[PDB]
Amino acid sequence: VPLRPMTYKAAVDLSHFLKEKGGLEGLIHSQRRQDILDLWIYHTQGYFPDWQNYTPGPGVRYPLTFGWCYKLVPEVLEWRFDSRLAFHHVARELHPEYF
Amino acid sequence: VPLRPMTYKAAVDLSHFLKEKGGLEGLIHSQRRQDILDLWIYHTQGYFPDWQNYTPGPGVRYPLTFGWCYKLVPEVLEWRFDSRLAFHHVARELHPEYF
Image (cartoon, rainbow over all chains, first blue to last red; front, side, top):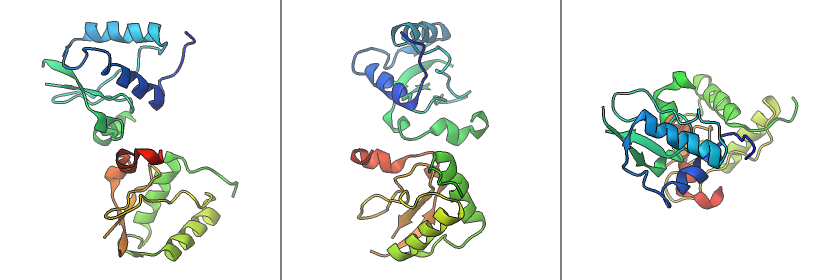
């Protein structure tokens, strides 16, 4: 599918789709796992795999892409959904440098 | 100045400018007062005066425009600044209908 962009719209439609039809919720996090997810989406939906970044730790890793509603919570981490993320751009609040 | 749009960028630059050089902070709210502010900005900076809407009450009136960081708190209200507004689109969280 046409190489498209990761807009806030996309980030939710997709963020949503992963909850209502999938076991990402809870699933322990690993770089390799993220990559197959990232590579998959990129092929399935078409978004270039470089948007799924989280804040640097320690603690909770808030997504850098507003709209994407999944943070990584406890360094063993899990894919924890959270919809106040679809409205609160936490990661920008904490790390304004990144934006 | 060229009739421009009220983008999140503008909404803060402007939202900021009002704190660091003005007594809007606290000032009791009235429709008429808002209007002279709205009409002024529109002339000064150039933004068509129809962006400064807040949520319907009771209670706190969160701005409908993300970026604009001023809510109306207590029905006598005041122009109360708040920067977690530049990151949290509260009004969309509460009233998803409006968006």
